[PDB]
Each structure stands twice: as C-alpha cells, then as structure tokens.
Length: 120
Ligand SMILES: [Mg+2]
Image (cartoon, rainbow, N blue to C red; front, top):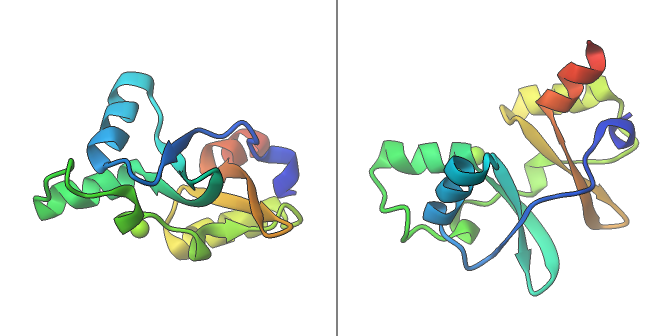
C-alpha cells in the first residue's frame, strides 16, 4: 500500500516562494518538487512540471508565486490505497507525485519512482 512506499521525509517550501526558487532547488539540489507550507501547515505541492508550464507560457518565474500554481485536491491519496490505485491516480491526473493525507493532514509524498522501484 501507499504507506509502505511513501516518503515521510518531505521537502518543503514557503507559500511566498516563487517558481524561480523551485527551479533553483531543482538545478542546485535535484529537488523535483516541494510541499508548500503556510504558517507551519502543509497545503499543497509545487513541481518542476509547474516550472515547465511557466516557461512554455513565457512567464517571469520570479513573479509566479507557488500558491498560484500549487495543487492539492486532485493529487492527494490515502496511505490505505494500494500501489496500483496510486499508479491509477497518477495516470488519470498525469502527475508523477501524490500527496499522502491522513487525518486531514499531509503526511508524506509518493512518487512514480517509488512505485517503479517497488515493482522491480
Ligand atoms: Mg498541474
């Protein structure tokens, strides 16, 4: 199940950060995503795909704040879901990562990389 393959040690970024920060975190530290935090509460996820979308639109990455592009509802899954169910949600929503929520709070992230490694 998701709880068996998820990562609880999540990378976070403040809600006031920009896509330039997300880009930098990827290029300098290899971080493909971050869980967005607002005053200590995890509220969504921002990813390098959001950066690519901004580049495609010609946006100034420093001016796009992470709250403008973060996601939560369609990318959240229960730790009780099976790995196949997690893969199905990733495929339906065309995302590489899902936020894992329990007791209304984000407790981790599961990525297609994790699922592929577990299958192998
Ligand atoms: Mg998106």
